[PDB]
Image (cartoon, helix red, strand yellow):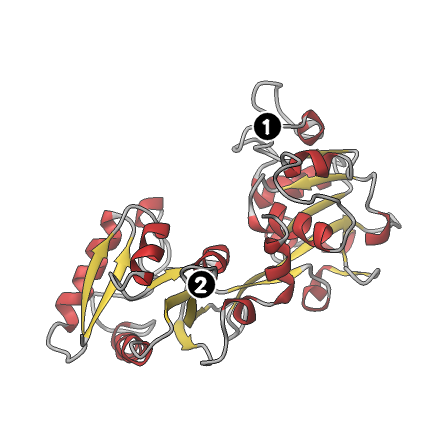
Amino acid sequence: KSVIRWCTVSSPEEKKCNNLRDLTQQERISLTCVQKATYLDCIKAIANNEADAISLDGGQVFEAGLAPYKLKPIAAEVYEHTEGSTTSYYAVAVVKKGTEFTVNDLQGKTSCHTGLGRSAGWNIPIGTLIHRGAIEWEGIESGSVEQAVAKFFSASCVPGATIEQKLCRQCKGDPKTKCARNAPYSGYSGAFHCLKDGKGDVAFVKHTTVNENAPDQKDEYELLCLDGSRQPVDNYKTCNWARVAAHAVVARDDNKVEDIWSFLSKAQSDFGVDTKSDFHLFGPPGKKDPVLKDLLFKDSAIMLKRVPSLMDSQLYLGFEYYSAIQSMR
């Protein structure tokens, strides 16, 4: 069919897609919009030849590539902050300068996490330590990963934890809500404040968190690297626990990939970052309302690049990320 069926997951998103249909309908490859309830319904639909493409973040690209779907990334967003690379951010472990411990001495420390189930604050650090054998968890019949983590750190603040009391012990706030998912210490800024207030020895955040939160106090913090070193906050490119790839358009690996890329390439050429048109494929940024944010593509993306034909989901995401999320299942 010379028809790309884009899959959308909310009604503001379906609207943006239909506006892109109306603006390219007299192009030869046309667009059409299928709306499903969740991104997973869209993964099932692409795999069942019911729709053809959708943009997914790192962990949902991981999901899309598992059997039985075996969807592969075909184009990736590029943002201004990672300088033309298909990277969203790097996950780093932040410590106060002057403490002396390395990753080899982490057992028994206290920790600050952005929240349970979050990518940089839970899935990448804990999966990295399970993959390296520092934390022993063989799989869900054990019980929760929470019980495994609680035999490794002596106490933590993990907003959202429900199984182990230790995991909410370092959290700030009244007993009622200190460990809620929206607590004082949740999120990148709250995991950073947990570290700053001394309630944790390590915070698991991303590479921009000390810059966003304490740009004038960078010198008081260091990064814990996986090889045993500690390095300055600015050295995240050589001291990170994993690179988290950019959002990627996923598709079935088949002859329609060139048609989807041909659509997107003309579409961004006309409606990309520098368009004079009313329609913008990417944003523009600054939408406040969450249901209006990042419709179809991220509002902060500046172009799309096609991913080499030979990169599957494991190669696109990278070994560190892939083995870490693999270990959490």
The quadrant in which residue 251 appears is bottom left
Few, some or many C-alpha atoms within 10 Å of disc 1 (few <14, some 14-19, many ≥20)? some
The vertical placement of 99 against 43, above or below, is: above
Front residue of 58/180: it is: 58
Where 190 sits versus 327, above or below? above
Q: Amino acid at mark 2?
A: His
Q: CA distance from mark 2 to mark 1?
A: 30 Å
What is the x, y in percent for residue 324? Answer: 64, 55
Q: Nearer the viewer, residue 288 or 310?
A: 310
In the picture, measured across the screen, residue 112 lies left or right of residue 261, that is: right
Q: Which residue is mark 2?
A: 247
Residue 9 visible in the snapshot? yes
> In the visual, does 154 lie left or right of 288?
right
Q: Is residue 193 above or below residue 11?
A: above
Which residue appears at 59% of the width and 61% of the height? Answer: 322
The residue that label 1 is drawn on is 162
Q: Is residue 90 above or below residue 85?
A: above
Please state the total of marks drawn on the protein image: 2
